[PDB]
Amino acid sequence: GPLGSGSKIKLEIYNETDMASASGYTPVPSVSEFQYIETETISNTPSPDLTVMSIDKSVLSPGESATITTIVKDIDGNPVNEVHINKTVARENLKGLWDYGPLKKENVPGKYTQVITYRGHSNERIDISFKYAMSFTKEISIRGRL
Image 1 (tube, helix red, strand yellow):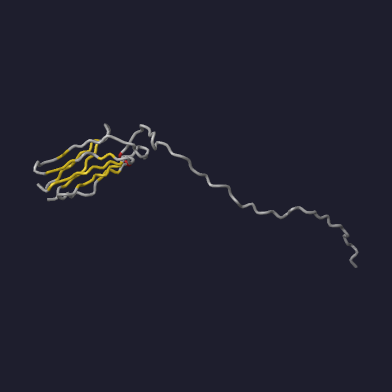
Image 2 (cartoon, rainbow, N blue to C red):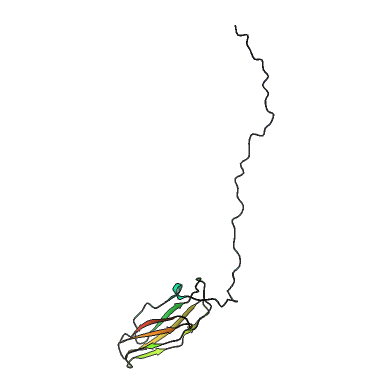
């Protein structure tokens, strides 16, 4: 019969803390901080490549005005505090009654706006060359609707 028995005493482990509570929570996400150039802006460099200076209305009725929207931006794409903008009138006729108001310089970042008014005397086109800072120059189109 089977006499080759082991009779070995099973050496076992006492409390091995096998079970492990699941640590599965994270810390807080990284936040932000305050901003500069909000008041004490720096004299950096602008670049109209990232600037939106346009007017989408080549129509001027006797009584209304067209406002050209120029938002100047830096070369880095930040809000320009302010630049210089001059007018330049490209005209063929003198029959037209083009009312050129002053350039409205608002408290807004890079946003310049100017209202060009027209009286219905003639029906032609007039382009206004906006001379920015002594670096870049642009030009917009005003069209009189008689």
